[PDB]
Length: 310
Ligand SMILES: NC(=O)c1ccc[n+]([C@@H]2O[C@H](COP(=O)([O-])OP(=O)(O)OC[C@H]3O[C@@H](n4cnc5c(N)ncnc54)[C@H](OP(=O)(O)O)[C@@H]3O)[C@@H](O)[C@H]2O)c1
Ligand SMILES: O=C(O)COc1cc(F)ccc1C(=S)NCc1ccc(Br)cc1F
Ligand SMILES: [Br-]
Image 1: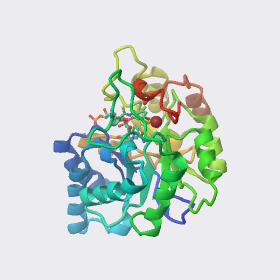
Image 2: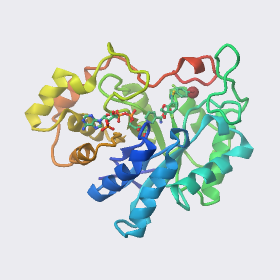
Image 3: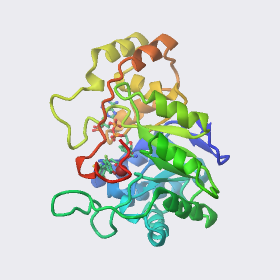
């Protein structure tokens, strides 16, 4: 159930995603998740619901359903806080909202820094994101200070490409390696190259959008649908599991961590029942064969930023 990180701590390979979980639903979703066995929650300041996630975590700690040591709580530094003097405050606001005194893991959410201010996506008058001149290496140094102040147990990265991971690994005076790179990964975007690179460096990969993010706000009717793919359905049927359960077990068997999102109690529970079956090697290779380099998480307004990863 857990994978060992290069900071010496163990991380549950299944967690609960919280992007798009409505603030009026996510407290119950996290309560239900902890009650049915989840011990890892994936959060972010930009999701605008950390307060409500925190109410759930705190209630389950108060009720003594779980111990703090048994939970693995992850959050992420938003792009408008990649300045030396803003990183600690950004982390502290997340801690405050989550009702925590430390994070198990804190990630640079995207490699690109944006102009600080109230807006999460500051734009120029023609719709391009406004960058910050801060680079990935100085942001990493700021992350390392959070470990040394006790605010976070591990630090990592998200949406970093091969060359950006390499830039951190080659950083002069590197003090802590990234523990995790959290990236989009599913049968339509299998990520074999970047996963093999990160794993070879001892960086654990977390697969986001493992179900293809059907609730992403920019979904279009014509788009591919993992959950409705009859080939994946057939694998599920053969194992008497749901398609979602196959899509969650797939990254687990690649030695990835996976963070499916749901606010539906029945689905939260279903999605956890993935430790009692095995996909065959042939099943695994067949799922890998569906790769189409189809990315659900990309954003035109940020594509000219110097550090846009894709
Ligand atoms: N690091 C980053 O840049 C980044 C980017 C994207 C995502 N993430 C993280 O990864 C998490 C997962 O990705 P995601 O939210 O994009 O999408 P996802 O987990 O691939 O899909 C979530 C969607 O699947 C539905 N669903 C869940 N379980 C289901 C089941 N058993 N059967 C049928 N439908 C099911 C959910 O519906 P209901 O909720 O209505 O049940 C929701 O609409 C996020 O929430 C976030 O924590 C990180
Ligand atoms: O980002 C998430 O976790 C999930 O997605 C989001 C979640 C939010 F709460 C707000 C925006 C996003 C978007 S639009 N993310 C895409 C995106 C952002 C920044 C850069 Br650089 C590139 C890029 F592709
Ligand atoms: Br970016």
